[PDB]
Length: 267
Length: 266
Ligand SMILES: [Cl-]
Ligand SMILES: [Cl-]
Image (cartoon, rainbow over all chains, first blue to last red; front, side, top):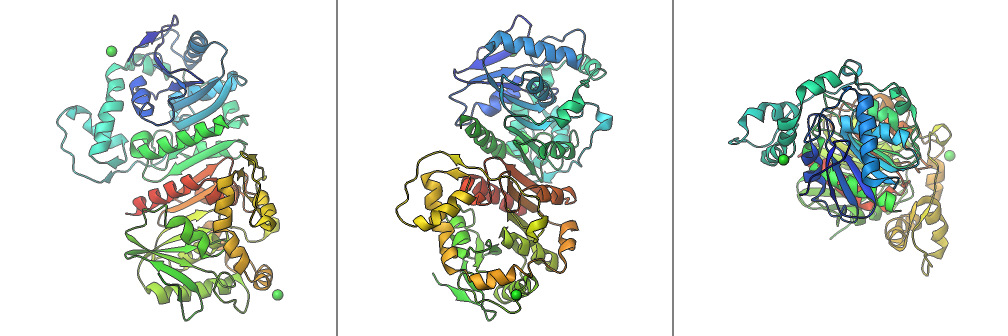
């Protein structure tokens, strides 16, 4: 597909016309993870799908200062270049979901809806309430290609079978291969927004939907559940046998629920 | 096909062979509400599907005393007769999901799994945390048949369209026509289990999945979110634009999640 680059040096794909969806991928991943996942699903066709590479990931340059504040500013700049003041839908995974929240919180009137998978809500890892990873070993797998990533797959994915390994290689490996680890490490020294507590308390005035796994040792599920009651339009799906690579563990659930979420907005 | 009756005077359907699924319906409904919904939306094929009419509802006789404790007792008798000691899966809607919880608590070693839609957790209506009901008026409906039932459809369902009205007529009205209002009215005076608090604190040691709706004014969602708090195998689906007739508002979602649940257990 055709890769574009904003003047703010954010690499992205843009496909389709109609209401924009801005997809923000997880930490160490890239737009392959989002693009390859959502393009196959029946009802994103009517939308303009915009898959960004975060700074220091994919084909997007690292940025100085290497802080979450600068990431947010750069992504806001980027979105304006791409769609201007047109109203948009947000999708976010992991740190992508943290930034999705920050954007929704700052561009309240321009945001139509937010859908998050395994989102970061507390940036500081030492503060997070996390779950316990496990494996459900469904099938024997004999890896040929990408053998060197197999442990990370096993350490991250919950449901272990051939399709999950194929998905990991297709969606996760590309980002791992491009991530700027030094940039990420520096970012993590200035990772938490000063308004993080506001994100934890805000009652968004549009659909706000979260999918979390019981076995997600990176961001867990508790803190996300706590966002739900006070969010008037807050939805949650929390599932067993599901971890941080929730979109592989529960491929079909994410497709189903993303579609159901678009239905909400369509109404 | 065939309708069955236990020695305990519980009316039921039982379809297929295999691991048993015991389906419990909501208050005032009957086993048409469960049977007609799940049999078509089915990855239920490899299971034995058992759809019970609760006492005083459907074609199951009322009981004395008319208390939830005794409703539970009757149901335990019924299950033991129908499946003995076989391990089983539980489905419960609303009052049926309250009973389901009780059953799983009582038959903890036999219960493989519990799937609940809009479950009663606190029986006492005056103590429940509930949502605000709304309608999403998608189409005009000009009812011809069952016009006298239309108010309660509007009052309960959230998503209002013609399909929702057809489903309501096929799923909810048969139970309405059969319910023993006198039993139910009496049952509602001894509605809490004597052990009710123990249900609110159990950490079930098998998958325990709940679907709830933001706009459910009957049982809400908050108490159910809190159960997921202390359940290590707790799952929850909480959706907007959804009320107490969740199987009608979110028909696809229920079949999807119930299939997923079965897979979880398999
Ligand atoms: Cl490339
Ligand atoms: Cl009485």
